[PDB]
Image (cartoon, rainbow over the protein chains, first blue to last red):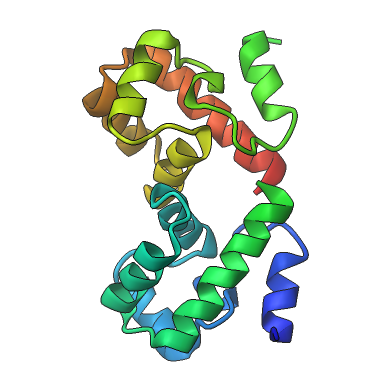
Length: 88
Length: 89
């Protein structure tokens, strides 16, 4: 199952969408990601790609960086993996 | 058209699983050094480009430090990634 936020993100190029457009990234996570430099969704894509799309390492990185719980990191990972399947 | 044909081929389409050597500026010598550091597909170098917020100075320095790229190689790689992003990101 997926959210509309997920479907909206995976349907099109992300351009300069803010980090909060990613599935799983709410206002609280988004704030903390922004304070650490990850202010646009593509910067988080960048980390996903630097980590060679590794689910365990990306989701652990997200937890360590902004405090994402397991559902939030699942949602964020899945939306980036599906976006990459469609556009990369 | 100022760019290389290799730039043109790269920016014309999604990169998928293309190797790092498909990037403009990344010949076989630079490509093997990138692979040895774990940057084995073009998308991993895109990742670093994006994590650095597409900043030219930081990206070109990173490339120099990571594989010894000269100024022309680093400008070509940066420009190829920048135009790819403008087309597809």
